[PDB]
Length: 256
Length: 256
Ligand SMILES: O=c1nc(NO)ccn1[C@@H]1O[C@H](COP(=O)(O)O)[C@@H](O)[C@H]1O
Ligand SMILES: O=c1nc(NO)ccn1[C@@H]1O[C@H](COP(=O)(O)O)[C@@H](O)[C@H]1O
Ligand SMILES: [Cl-]
Ligand SMILES: [Cl-]
Image 1 (cartoon, each protein chain N blue to C red):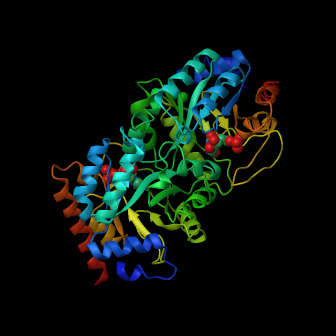
Image 2: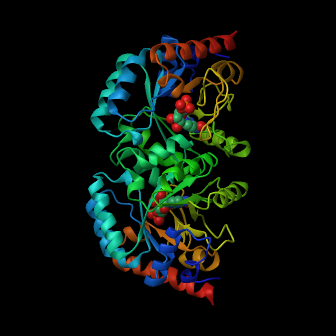
Image 3: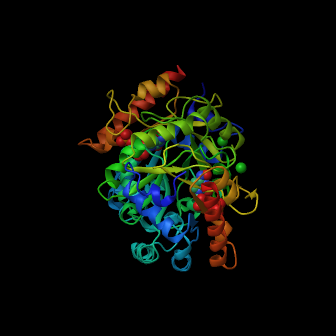
């Protein structure tokens, strides 16, 4: 079990994973904020206020009512100032020829500003191969969806194993997984886990929740992704701090 | 085998599926153009020129460099003048609360203009449940992705069967499937098949092509989806007519 700091130095580490690991160590945070908001001013207010507490901000640019590239330019200034990576949760899941265009072009120009994106593995490795053509020149990384937090998820068994294999065969671009627990023993790969809250439960339209101690300390994941557990709290600063301390202490416990 | 006209009257038949089947009958076309272009001017010129040859125009709004809602308003007008449905190939693939905002809101407001959208089934029925909450009041329909055309597709076997059962359980919203062949015996469901060209082959990023005669005649799908086979030809109108004749003649042949 290596520290984040030491994994940032592994000979085979991807530069983006290495950059994320060094900043998680420096800032003592393994918390990704799911910035699930509809206005650009909310997204920038949250990134500025909660930046110090997080290693990563996860966006859904396609839910922003007033997206412009100038919003993303301002987000990058905040990511650079407070030191976190930007993860656009686009869940690419088309053939390689189409995802390449969806990643580089259209109105969002996602590769122009997202350090990380994710993809489903259901199309086969072409999905990774098309993204890579755009993301490698721009020094970008991708996470593959190995498992899902939601009820009825088909991302189990042989499907998870295919995501892991795909990741090993594309490690110049794939830096880890979205998953509910550690799915690879290779320490170069990051594991990010959504469906996290301090309290048990907690469905609604299919989502399921586990605590930071369970997913970090017991299930061996690296980073927790939290949206509503922070964003719906009265005091989002205190809430972000609670999740950061929970996830950081669970990670320390695991190192022994 | 029922004709398209007759299927338009199955009792169990969605009104969107009915509208589509009647216009396929009337126009003698079971061709969906995949309008994979990056400029509004080209998208709308193809929509107008090829409108008479197709039953459906399939978009990737997120690759359109000069997207505005005014462009989609013009597309609706051509869909009404020429009679074809608009299918946004967004491959929704997220938890329920997320996909509902991806469908209704953001800059694209997909539900406001797209007759049809599609979704992956990997997250479980939560994906359909989120879209359906938006789509039912707006009298929209959805396709589920039961199979994929690309090398390495994990949409096979139990996965595909999971997709069919999900469509059965959400039949007031789900109008059929994206798949390589007939996956359901119910004639109320439509089957639309991408990965189609007159020539055997593939691209350099995992796309595989089969002929109209193979997919409509032998595999018993309903509609061919064709992008490059048409968009790359010098005369896209001639090309769309070749594909329309081929798919329609193949449909006649399966009817005896
Ligand atoms: O990163 C993810 N990986 C997923 N695969 O399981 C699924 C959802 N997500 C996103 O993680 C966020 C979790 O939010 P809540 O903590 O339930 O409010 C949402 O924006 C989801 O769309
Ligand atoms: O190729 C696909 N395969 C699918 N499943 O295999 C689903 C949709 N598509 C879309 O179908 C179109 C096929 O394009 P070509 O016909 O391969 O240019 C593209 O826009 C793809 O994104
Ligand atoms: Cl890597
Ligand atoms: Cl491939």
